[PDB]
Amino acid sequence: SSLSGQVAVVTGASRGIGAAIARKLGSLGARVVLTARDVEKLRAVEREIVAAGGEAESHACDLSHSDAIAAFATGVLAAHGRCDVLVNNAGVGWFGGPLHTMKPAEWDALIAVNLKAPYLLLRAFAPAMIAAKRGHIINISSLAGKNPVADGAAYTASKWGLNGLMTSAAEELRQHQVRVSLVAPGSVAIEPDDIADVVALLATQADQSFISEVLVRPTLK
Amino acid sequence: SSLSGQVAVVTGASRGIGAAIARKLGSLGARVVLTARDVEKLRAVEREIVAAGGEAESHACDLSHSDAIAAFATGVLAAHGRCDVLVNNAGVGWFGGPLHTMKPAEWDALIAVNLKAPYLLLRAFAPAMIAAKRGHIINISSLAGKNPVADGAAYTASKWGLNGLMTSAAEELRQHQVRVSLVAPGSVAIEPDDIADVVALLATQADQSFISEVLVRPTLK
Amino acid sequence: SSLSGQVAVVTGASRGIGAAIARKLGSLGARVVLTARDVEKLRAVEREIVAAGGEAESHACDLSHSDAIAAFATGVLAAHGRCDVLVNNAGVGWFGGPLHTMKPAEWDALIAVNLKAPYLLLRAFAPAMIAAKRGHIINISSLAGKNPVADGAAYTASKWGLNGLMTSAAEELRQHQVRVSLVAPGSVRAIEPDDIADVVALLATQADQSFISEVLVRPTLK
Amino acid sequence: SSLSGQVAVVTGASRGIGAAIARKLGSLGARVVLTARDVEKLRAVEREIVAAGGEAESHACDLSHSDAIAAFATGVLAAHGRCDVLVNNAGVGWFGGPLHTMKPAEWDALIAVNLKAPYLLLRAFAPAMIAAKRGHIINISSLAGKNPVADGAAYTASKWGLNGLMTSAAEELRQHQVRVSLVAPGSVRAIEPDDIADVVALLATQADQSFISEVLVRPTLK
């Protein structure tokens, strides 16, 4: 198998894109560490991966708590000694209305998960990737830094912010042979498996190859 | 005078771009409400504005505290009944090293000022601008959403995030005749007065005119 | 006023944005050299400039030919010896269908005007601006380089192309005190000709030290 | 392997990226139609493809002429009846000086190859792809649309132009199951030809449902 002997951490793995990425990496032989808030929705996906012949485990982790993320990483690295693929996929939305109508607590909840947690996760897993001189950090971004979403202002800030965050970290980590990439829409409707296929393509590149960004347009009809 | 009878709030007004924007708007007749952390550096600038014949006042405000920002806005609107120009200029930097080396508390301090405070300020002053169907919110962004800064990853995230935030809020507010604009570098070295001149140009547009973004390249030699 | 004794070239100056930019520049005291395919469409705008007490001449310039652009600039320089303000405003459209149905002759007509003419104009006037150590070249772009127009593929290319062409020339000419700028829309989704004319006014009359390189404009407030 | 019984056109296929893309596509079982100004520079690459047991033909195509591109595509279609993979890879450079010193003939040579040829090629092969309800058009772009090259102004225009041209054509052709894509650099600041060839391989062999529209590549890990 392409990813046999590897460990893959997928956030927001309970449904949709996250679930599909989990199954895909599991089918290639990676041991998939699934995380989300709801353990029960995770277990369905854990069972499917195992049923089809792969390895998977489930961990509740509240991504808005820094200590919780450090506890989660410490457990994963203590149990398996490595993380080959970190997929930043967990995301929240807020589309209630204009930015002045957004409460600070709603701002905090959205930025904590969409922007701060991918930084915390990279901070928790990158030092191990550096020491091993290998690994992928792959970020699912639902906006390409181009068009604002009226009534989704904080949301937009978090995605363009993620893009700038991870584009910068890519220049920092490449000297240690660690690869940070971005997956984003190339239009403006995408089947989860297509994004899963892109992540699989990223995680199985030749050693020297460094694809930094893939833009995907809606599945054909 | 072009801005006579108007109130202009300028954040980070104690030195450089902020100071220069303060003096410029003061010279056009605006009453300038200066804010920063250090009251003493503010007073020098307050004295210059008054010395040259304008009106100005100084207020310490810690932009990383939401309540402090609401207290500050409440005072300004209670004292003058209006805010015609809000300039988001206060900014912090962090260029210590790669993103995994950045401490969460340093992340928090940078994002609180560069990204959350401009949202809090818009939230505190926009409702008054909406009710009056007029006003400018002008954001000084030191990056145009284009090039990452290695070793300034959080910093980059905060500027691209600001851009997406304010581009979205511009679509929301325009229906109430309130105008959100962005000033940013167009290259890659800029004299503070040139940025001050751009802000003055934004604050004095024809009613109907909506310049949303100005890119500025280094002062000529 | 501000631009007294300057000459401003303005292409596609017979209506809309070009017309307004013409009127706005003349009203600030610049002599407005106007351009269009046909000299008769220009008379109306030339009249409004004079009537308000500014100077204005009219030339037929076919922007699809180099020779034509060369002869046109030669004349302007022989007559006045300077060009202070070159406004690349003329453009064509093509939205007939998908790219593969577009014929080479249509491609050529669109690219010649939208992408090649602004270069030729810059080439013909930049020497005088460089020698004089001052000048503005201002470009009106209907696309900001972000979103594609389906069934306007060549049109899209010509605009993103223009943005790249003039962003680069701007770096080349800074050293000579010549300022190249762009004006483009600020949203994907409606803009009053005067809003643009005002922005152009603003660029044409900046402080010498300052260099505004791009201005994005959103639809006029209603 | 993956591409058995397909035909892949590859322009500028005599060395570097084009050479590698050629080898990589042949090794997956596609018949590789190679292009260059001169048919002799192609023999080496054609030999490597056959030697490894793939098929490959060589044509001299002068991309600066429409007729030439038309005659070239006509031949390929008469000979095989399909083009599965069109790789727009050939390009020229010009970095002689600032835009105003660039002569119209040099402008024309650069634009004809960099911007007009990819359109002409797409126009000549898209009809067959549309009829067949499958096909890839893959474009190699050396600029991502963000940063200007001072003293490479026309070059810059041709690349940002290409990005806009092909982003638009991609929207036009989705409905017919034809997939247009871009490959470009991921940093302002050095990339192994095989990295590109691999990405092209990846695009050429996607699932039918999927549509990757752009791939950015950073310099090869050292």
Image: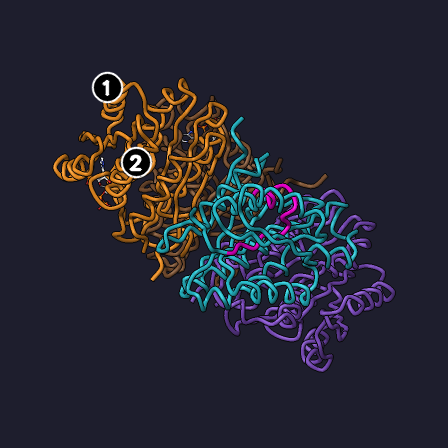
Chain colours: A orange, B brown, C purple, D cyan
Q: Is residue A62 left or right of residue C10?
A: left
Q: Position of residue C141 (x, y in %)?
A: 58, 60
Q: Residue at x 75, y 47 (%)?
A: D98
Placement of C26 over or under A172, stated as above or below = below
In depth, the one of C114 and B81 nearer the eye is: C114
**Along the horizontal axis of the image, is D48 left or right of D25?**
right
Residue under label 1: A79
- Local secondary structure at mark 2: loop
Chain part drawn in magenta: D7-20
Q: Mark 2 lies on which chain?
A: A
Q: For the residue carrying disc 1, how many other residues have a C-alpha within 10 Å: few (<14), some (14-19), or many (20+)?
A: few
The alpha-carbon separation of the residues under discs 2 and 1 comes to 21 Å
**As shown in the figure, which amino acid type bears the numbered disc 2?**
Leu
Which mark is drawn over residue A28?
2
Residue A170 is marked as none
Chain of the residue under label 1: A
Nearer to the camera, A220 or A50: A50
Marks 2 and 1 belong to one chain: yes
Asked if residue D192 is positioned above or below residue B137 in the image, the reply reads above
> Residue D8 in magenta?
yes
Residue furthest bottom in the image: C40
